[PDB]
Image (spheres, grey):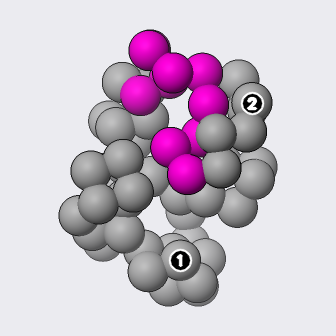
Amino acid sequence: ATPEELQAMDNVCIICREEMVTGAKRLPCNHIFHTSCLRSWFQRQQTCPTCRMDVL
Ligand SMILES: [Zn+2]
Ligand SMILES: [Zn+2]
């Protein structure tokens, strides 16, 4: 992800509602989340942790 896109969304991972300073990806829906929270989130819920919009 980029610093401009992260700041455009509080650069905070919703999944755990913490913070994202480095080590995360960006979804095609405009929602960045921890690279660990995602792979683990989709493993149970195939929907964005915010927009729950099919991505996989
Ligand atoms: Zn997280
Ligand atoms: Zn989304």
Residue count near mark 2 (Cα–Cα under 10 Å), binned few <14, some 14–19, many ≥20: few
Q: Quadrant of the N terminus?
A: bottom right
> Is 47 included in the stretch rendered in magenta?
yes
Residue beneath label 1, please? 9
**Residue closer to the observer: 49 or 1:** 49
Residue lying furthest top: 43
Image position of 41 (left or right of 28): left
Q: Provide residue 23's location: percent of width, then percent of height.
A: 34, 54
Q: In this rendering, is residue 48 above or below 27?
A: above
Q: In this rendering, is residue 23 above or below 48?
A: below
Q: Provide residue 24's location: percent of width, then percent of height.
A: 42, 53
What residue is shown at x 73% (from left), y 39% (from top)? 53
Q: Provide residue 44's location: percent of width, then percent of height.
A: 44, 15
What residue is shown at x 44% (from left), y 80% (from top)? 10
* Res. 56 mark: none
Can residue 6 be seen from the camera position used here?
yes
Can residue 25 be seen from the camera position used here?
no
- How many marks do you count on the picture? 2
> Is 40 included in the stretch rendered in magenta?
no
Q: Disc 2 marks which amino acid? A: Asp
Q: Secondary structure at mark 1?
A: loop
Q: Disc 1 marks which amino acid? A: Met
The quadrant holding residue 47 is: top right
Image position of 38 (left or right of 18): right
Q: Which residues are magenta?
A: 41-50
Residue beneath label 2, please? 54
Q: Quadrant of the C terminus?
A: top right
**Residue closer to the observer: 52 or 24:** 52
Report, in whole angstroms, how far the alpha carbon at label 1 lies from the one at label 2. Answer: 20 Å
Magenta stretch, main secondary structure, is loop
Q: Secondary structure at mark 2?
A: loop
**Residue closer to the observer: 55 or 22:** 55
